């Protein structure tokens, strides 16, 4: 069928299923070999010749087709994965000027839309999230003064919505990436994460919210938050989260932190409490 | 620092003579906040509004906020441009960064005392590099302070017109509010005492919030057609009092949304990026907001909601009424106290009906008279079955805070009224099933209900010649003793037991141990 | 309900003898008997669909059963039993209201006048 329709991706899904099973035939190939079904080979003919061609882009959904077909491969997935990555990253293409002084970002400004983002599979999704996390932590450890590409931060915001990935998503991010970015002492990536927290999510579970608020008080108090932008960001997020708490969830949430109330409230600012 | 200055400013304005001095003071305040950018406006207004003054000082600070917001043309020429060149839906577009560039180059923002640096006569330049800003501006940083100052203005009586003009000039800021409906619900449910008498202010508030976001969202997302047609117009000393059809329509929309319909009374949305996880929650909140904002007092609204199902009303088909009971209970439990408090008076009225006290024509089981499932056949006798069903439904969907108000009502109002055995059976059927919840959450209520039941039994026994259903009563008391109360209600029981008729004493020996 | 559904044209003697036989088979008080008869007639009337069946049901329940009651009087004290059954029936307000609103008239008054005509 035609490629422009997202439902046709569902149509190709069974084909990709077979590919994955053949990938499980990569090891122990001498046991239980299952031949190709009769009608699937015509469909299978298209994907391989698509793989051989070197003209692949988001105009059609063949990039997502390749990702779904070869996510479980270490050599066939690397070409589509990169092909998305430099497009949403702008690997040195240009230095676009952000508002204010000394703010330089990459030239990529177009992220993946919802239809394309929802045309992928869970494994390709987590691989992309892991790749994005690795490069952003790499930038944080390299002490880069260059602001990250706007397209990739929009993609970062759009990839945390999915509820099925909380094992790899918000929990892992808050537990690991935020303390490591804080310990890297960059405060640029830290500011981007803080502003993303502020205006780019709606559904966050209450214990994640209270943990994030405790993190803000920890980071807010020490680590010389005397710069105007940092305190404004921290001040803004301290009021945005507090004023958005649910009515019937605060009671079962704060009863967990009764022993040490100092971690959920500030000392310098009376406005917060 | 800023709070002390805020206190000083209000004290100064409490001592500042009205006239040209006030105008120049508000102009120079505007100049400091923005022409030199010493402090962002939001922090200064939050510090001004976080004061605990008494008397005229509160009015002075409120009026200073009013003059700092609307008088200044410069503040206005930014929010209008922002709301004209941006939309709340961000996930559906890919050209936001350049629009941000255009808006920010139209009005540069200074956060490192830039404007204060340039105005210094010696050349002062800032060299500290900034940090990446992708979403920040003064309007979005000011929005929560705007909500909180709306709350502060509602806390005080003579500043209603300032609220009206503030809304009429800055209603556009709420196009980008993430959860406006819940904010309205909490604000209207929290300030009901201060808003029962000022219907015009409440109408203005709800109208401004709904009309702020009447373009992006599809038609008929929050308000019904009849309310948007009749009550939307300005009042003329004849507020639009509705008939029962309006309430029937609201309850029907909720049961159709919750039951599941392919077309649906509410247009579908992407729940991933909204504030309401489910269509049912969204429907409940908007229905509560629309019903609570009327100019009619709570008693009549609650009585009409109950009479939707009590009185013989078409448009409510049979064999589907349990869903209507469900919708009524869910709606009435979220409303404030004056609305749902009418159920006690309804129970008091039905317990005094002649069919329970004198007309005892039905000699058979009253047990099947109170079984509402008997509605399968045409045995809906009187309001007794319907009121019993609503009491069960309302108390099921209520929290322990609402249920804790029951024992005082039981021991104060119903105690001197029950004389015959049918009324005793009615109150047993009414109270029995919720002893589980009471024992789970509040044991004192359990003690009170047990002693009230024993006292009621003694009163009926003293004032009645004989009891034809003593065996079910004894079985129920034994079940209560061996399941819920244990052996905690002991001391107060022997005095009541010792004064009863000898047959009851013979059949209640084991209660005392 | 079964008699009113199919064999509305049958002779009332069979219906009367069947009703008396059922009354003798299981001990039934007279007010309960009459109340059950009236309630069955009304509930059969309400559920009838629009058409000639509604007319047939109305004709049955407002013409035929008075002769059944008259024959019960003749074969058999009955007057106060009928009054007691009627005061039981009058307690049911929603059933009477639905029957009244379906036929667009106060059917209780017409039924009372018709039974008064029979004495």
Image: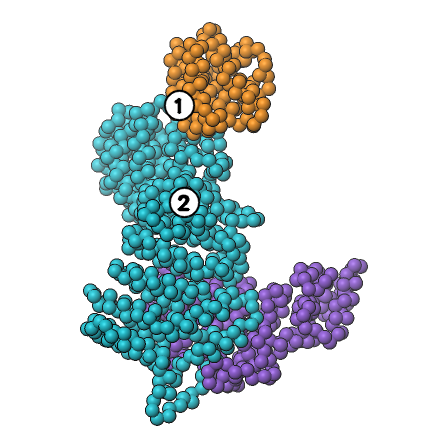
Chain colours: A purple, B cyan, C orange
| Residue A269 image offset from top left, x and y in percent | 32, 74
Q: At x 56% / y 20%, what residue is drawn?
A: C56
Residue tagged 2 = B329
| Residue A97 image offset from top left, x and y in percent | 52, 83
Do we see residue B497 in this rendering?
A: no
Do we see residue B430 in this rendering?
A: yes
| Residues at marks 1 and 2 touching, judged by CB atoms closer than 8 Å | no
Specify the subunit that label 2 lies on.
B
Quarter of the image with the N terminus of chain B in it: bottom left
- Mark 1 lies on a secondary structure that is loop
Specify the subunit that label 1 lies on.
C
Which residue is situated farthest in the top direction here?
A: C74
Q: Quadrant of residue B354?
A: top left
Q: Is residue C57 left or right of residue B65?
A: right
Q: Is residue B494 left or right of residue B331?
A: left
Residue tagged 1 = C90
Which residue is situated farthest in the bottom direction here?
A: B122
Q: Is residue A90 left or right of residue B38?
A: right
Q: At x 43% / y 57%, what residue is drawn?
A: B210
As measured in the structure, the alpha-carbon distance from the residue carrying label 1 to the one carrying label 2 is 31 Å
Dot 1 crowding, Cα within 10 Å, few <14, some 14–19, many 20+:
some
Name the foreground residue: B26 vs B380: B26
């Amino acid at each position: 069928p035609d490629i422009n329709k997202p439902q046709s991706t569902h149509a190709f899904a069974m084909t990709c299923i077979w590919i994955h099973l053949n990938r499980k035939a990569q090891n122990d190939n001498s046991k239980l070999q299952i031949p190709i079904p009769h009608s699937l080979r015509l469909h299978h003919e298209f994907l391989q010749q698509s793989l051989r061609n070197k003209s692949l882009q988001m105009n059609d959904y063949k990039i997502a087709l390749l990702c779904n077909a070869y996510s479980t491969n270490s050599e066939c997935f690397t070409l589509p994965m990169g092909a998305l990555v430099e497009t949403i990253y702008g690997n040195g293409i240009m230095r676009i000027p952000l508002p204010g002084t000394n703010c330089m970002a990459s030239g990529s400004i177009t992220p993946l839309p919802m239809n394309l983002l929802d045309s992928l599979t869970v494994h390709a999704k987590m691989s992309l999230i892991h790749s994005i996390a690795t490069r952003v932590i790499k930038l944080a450890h390299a002490k880069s003064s260059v602001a990250l590409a706007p397209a990739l931060v929009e993609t970062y915001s759009r990839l945390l919505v999915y509820m099925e990935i909380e094992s790899l998503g918000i929990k892992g991010f808050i537990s690991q990436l935020l303390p490591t970015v804080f310990k890297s002492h960059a405060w640029g990536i830290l500011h981007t994460l803080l502003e993303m927290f502020s205006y780019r999510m709606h559904h966050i579970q209450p214990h994640y919210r209270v943990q994030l608020l405790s993190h803000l008080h920890t980071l807010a108090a020490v680590a010389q938050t005397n710069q105007n932008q940092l305190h404004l960001c921290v001040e803004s997020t301290a009021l945005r989260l507090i004023t958005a708490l649910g009515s019937s969830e605060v009671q079962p949430q704060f009863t967990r932190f009764l022993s040490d109330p100092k971690t959920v409230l500030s000392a310098e600012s009376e406005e917060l409490n | 620092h800023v709070r002390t200055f805020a206190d000083f400013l209000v004290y100064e304005f409490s001592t500042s003579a009205g006239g040209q001095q006030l105008n120049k003071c508000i102009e120079i305040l505007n100049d400091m906040v923005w022409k030199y950018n010493i402090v962002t406006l939001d922090r200064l207004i939050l510090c001004l509004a976080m004061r605990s003054h008494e008397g005229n000082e509160a009015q002075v600070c409120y009026f200073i906020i009013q003059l700092l917001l609307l008088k200044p043309n410069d503040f206005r020429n930014r929010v209008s441009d922002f709301v004209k060149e941006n939309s709340p839906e961000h996930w559906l577009q890919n050209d936001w960064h350049t629009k941000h560039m255009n808006y920010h180059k139209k009005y540069p923002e200074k956060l490192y005392f830039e404007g204060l640096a340039e105005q210094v006569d010696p050349p002062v330049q800032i060299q500290s590099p900034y940090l990446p800003i992708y979403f920040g501006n003064v309007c979005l940083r000011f929005l929560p302070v705007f909500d909180i100052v709306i709350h502060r203005f509602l806390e005080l009586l003579p500043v209603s017109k300032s609220l009206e003009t503030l809304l009429d000039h800055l209603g556009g800021l709420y196009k980008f509010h993430d959860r406006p409906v819940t904010y309205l619900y909490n604000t209207l449910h929290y300030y009901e005492m201060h808003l029962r008498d000022r219907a015009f202010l409440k109408r203005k508030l709800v109208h401004a919030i709904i009309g702020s976001l009447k373009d992006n969202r599809p038609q008929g997302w929050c308000l019904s057609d009849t309310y948007l047609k009749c009550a939307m117009n300005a009042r003329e000393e004849n507020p639009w009092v509705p008939d029962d059809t309006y309430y029937c329509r609201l309850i029907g929309r909720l049961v159709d949304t919750m039951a599941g319909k392919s077309p649906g009374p509410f247009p579908n949305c992407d729940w991933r990026f909204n504030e309401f996880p489910n269509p049912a929650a969204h429907a409940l909140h908007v229905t509560c907001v629309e019903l609570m904002a009327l100019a009619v007092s709570g008693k009549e609204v609650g009585n009409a909601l109950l009479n939707v199902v009590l009185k013989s009303q078409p448009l409510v088909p049979r064999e589907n009424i349990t869903a209507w009971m469900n919708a009524i209970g869910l709606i009435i439990t979220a409303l404030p106290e004056p609305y749902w408090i009418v159920l006690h008076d309804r129970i008091v009225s039905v317990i005094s009906s002649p069919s329970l006290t004198s007309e005892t024509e039905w000699v058979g089981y009253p047990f099947r008279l109170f079984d509402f499932t008997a509605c399968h056949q045409s045995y809906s006798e009187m309001s007794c079955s319907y009121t019993l069903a609503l009491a069960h439904a309302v108390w099921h969907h209520s929290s322990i805070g609402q249920l804790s108000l029951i024992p005082k009502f039981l021991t104060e109002v119903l105690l001197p009224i029950v004389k015959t055995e049918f009324q005793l059976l009615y109150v047993y059927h009414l109270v029995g099933p919720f002893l589980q919840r009471f024992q789970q959450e509040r044991t004192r209520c359990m003690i009170e209900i047990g002693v009230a039941f024993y006292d009621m039994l003694l009163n009926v026994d003293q004032c009645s010649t004989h009891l034809n259903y003593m065996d079910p009563i004894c079985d129920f008391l034994y079940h209560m003793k061996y399941m819920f109360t244990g052996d905690s209600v002991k001391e107060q029981v022997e005095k009541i037991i010792c004064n009863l008729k000898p047959a009851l004493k013979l059949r209640l020996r084991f209660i005392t141990h | 309900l079964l008699e009113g559904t199919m064999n509305l044209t049958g002779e009332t003697q069979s219906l009367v003898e069947q009703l008396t036989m059922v009354k003798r088979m299981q001990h039934i008080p007279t007010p309960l008997f009459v109340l059950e008869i009236w309630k069955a007639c009304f509930v059969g009337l309400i559920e009838s669909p629009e058409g000639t069946e509604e007319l047939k049901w109305t004709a049955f329940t407002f013409l035929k059963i008075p002769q059944v009651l008259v024959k019960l009087k003749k074969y058999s004290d009955f007057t106060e039993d009928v009054n007691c059954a009627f005061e039981f029936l009058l307690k049911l307000t929603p059933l009477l209201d639905k029957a009244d609103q379906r036929c667009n008239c106060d059917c209780t008054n017409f039924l009372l006048q018709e039974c008064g005509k029979q004495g």
